[PDB]
Image (cartoon, rainbow, N blue to C red):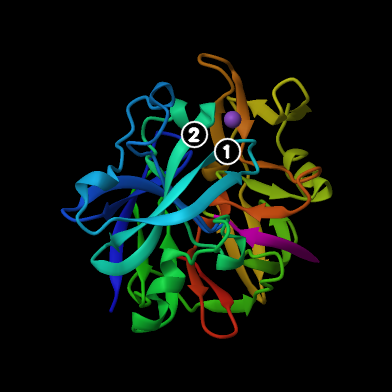
C-alpha cells in the first residue's frame, strides 16, 4: 500500500504545515501537524477542557463506531518550545492520503497549553519520530508510520514541504518526479529516538564551503533551522545590521535586507536554502526589525534541521531495518 497527502502552510510565514487525517468511522477529518521530531498522535477532542479549545476541529470518540478506550493508558508530552498536552487514549482507524491503519493509538487531549489553544489551525500532532519516544503509559504505543510499515510497498515516507505553498507527504513510495538529480542518503542514529544525522558542513551565500560535522535532527515540527552559534554568527555577519537580540529571543535583521542563501552538506551533496526562506518577517506587526530563520541551538542541546532547511529539499525518511535519511534538491 501507499498514501499521499497534501500538506499546507498554516500562515503566510510557513510557521507550520497541516495535513488532513481521517480518524474513526464515519471519518472525522482533523488537520494535524506531522512532526518527525516526536512520536505521539494526539488530537483536540470532546474531552479537551472547553476553555482550552478555540476554533480547532475536535475528535469525538463516542461518534466513532471503531473507537475503543485503551483502558488505563495516559499520555503527557512537552515540546522544545515549552508547549505541552496530556490526556487519555483510544484506538481507532486512522487514514492519511488513502493509507489506512487499524488499531492506531489516538491520544485524546484533556489539557493543552496556551500555544495550542491560540493556534486554531492545528487540530493535533501526528508524530513520525521513532516509537521509543512515544509517551503513552503504561504501554508505549507505535507511531502511524511504524504501524503502517509492514503494509507499505517500501518502508519509507517522504517530506516535500513547500515555500509559501502546499507540499506533500508520501508513504510507501518515492515519487521520482518530485526532485531533481539524485537522492543522497546519509546515516541515522536512533539512539535519542530522532531522525538524527550528521551534515558535512555549510556555506554562506556564495562563500566557500566549510567542511565540518554538524549532528542534528530532521524535524518537520520545528519551524526554523537551529545550528551551532559559530555557524549562525558566520551567517548573520553577512547581513548588514543583523544582531542577536536577547529581548526578542534571537537574531533579527533589517527588513530592508536581502538575505544570502545558506548551504548545508549531505555527504558530498549540497542543499541550498534560498535567502528568502530565512525571512520570518517583522518581529511585531509593522516593525522594521525582521526575525531570522537561522538561529542558534545553544542551550537547546541539539541542532535542528527544521522546516527552513527541509523545505529546500525532497527528504526521504527510510525506515528500513537500518534507517537512513535521503536528501535531493528540487
Ligand atoms: Na517567533
Residue 255 lies in what quarter of the image? top right
**SS of the residue at dot 2?**
strand
Q: Is residue 156 above or below residue 192?
A: below
Residue located 58% across and 25% down the image? 256
Give the residue at x 49% y 62%.
128
For the residues bearing labels 1 and 2, Cβ distance under 8 angstroms: yes
Residue 206 in sight in this render: no
Q: CA distance from mark 1 to mark 2?
A: 8 Å
| Pointer 2 residue | 111
Asked if residue 91 lies left or right of residue 261, the reply is: left
Q: Which mark is residue 84?
A: 1
Task: Please give the range of residues in magenta.
Answer: 211-219
**In the structure shown, which secondary structural element does the residue marked by tag 1 occupy?**
strand
Q: Residues within 10 Å of mark 1 (few under 14, many from 20)?
A: some
Task: Say which of marks 1 and 2 sits in front.
Answer: 2
Magenta-span inclusion, residue 239: no
Tell which quarter ligand 1 is in: top right
Position above or below: 206 against 229? below
Q: Residue 290, image x and y in percent?
A: 60, 26
Amino acid at each position: 500500500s501507499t498514501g499521499s497527502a497534501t500538506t499546507t502552510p498554516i500562515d503566510s510565514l510557513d510557521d507550520a504545515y497541516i495535513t488532513p487525517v481521517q480518524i474513526g468511522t464515519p471519518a472525522q477529518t482533523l488537520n494535524l501537524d506531522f512532526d518527525t521530531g516526536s512520536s505521539d498522535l494526539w488530537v483536540f477532542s470532546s474531552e479537551t477542557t472547553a476553555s482550552e479549545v478555540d476554533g480547532q476541529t475536535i475528535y469525538t470518540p463516542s461518534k466513532s463506531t471503531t473507537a475503543k478506550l485503551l483502558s488505563g493508558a495516559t499520555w503527557s508530552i512537552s515540546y522544545g518550545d515549552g508547549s505541552s498536552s496530556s490526556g487519555d487514549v483510544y484506538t481507532d482507524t486512522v487514514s492519511v492520503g488513502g493509507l489506512t491503519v487499524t488499531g492506531q493509538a489516538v491520544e485524546s487531549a484533556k489539557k493543552v497549553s496556551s500555544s495550542f489553544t491560540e493556534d486554531s489551525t492545528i487540530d493535533g500532532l501526528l508524530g513520525l519520530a521513532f516509537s521509543t519516544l512515544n509517551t503513552v503509559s503504561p504501554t508505549q504505543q507505535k507511531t502511524f508510520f511504524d504501524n503502517a510499515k509492514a503494509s507499505l510497498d517500501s518502508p519509507v515516507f517522504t517530506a516535500d514541504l513547500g515555500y509559501h505553498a502546499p507540499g506533500t507527504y508520501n508513504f510507501g513510495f518515492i515519487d521520482t518526479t518530485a526532485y531533481t538529480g539524485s537522492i543522497t542518503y546519509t546515516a541515522v542514529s536512533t539512539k535519542q529516538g530522532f531522525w538524527e544525522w550528521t551534515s558535512t558542513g555549510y556555506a554562506v551565500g556564495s562563500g566557500t564551503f566549510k567542511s565540518t560535522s554538524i549532528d542534528g535532527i530532521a524535524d518537520t515540527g520545528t519551524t526554523l533551522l537551529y545550528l551551532p552559534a559559530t555557524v549562525v554568527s558566520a551567517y548573520w555577519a553577512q547581513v548588514s545590521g543583523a544582531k542577536s537580540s536577547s529581548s526578542v529571543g534571537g537574531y533579527v535583521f533589517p527588513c530592508s535586507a536581502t538575505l544570502p542563501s545558506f548551504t548545508f552538506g549531505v555527504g558530498s551533496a549540497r542543499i541550498v536554502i534560498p535567502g528568502d526562506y530565512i525571512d520570518f518577517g517583522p518581529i511585531s506587526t509593522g516593525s522594521s526589525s525582521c526575525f531570522g530563520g537561522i538561529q542558534s541551538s545553544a542551550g537547546i542541546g541539539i541542532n535542528i534541521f527544521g522546516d527552513v532547511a527541509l523545505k529546500a529539499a525532497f527528504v526521504v525518511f527510510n525506515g528500513a531495518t537500518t534507517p537512513t535519511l535521503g536528501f535531493a534538491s528540487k
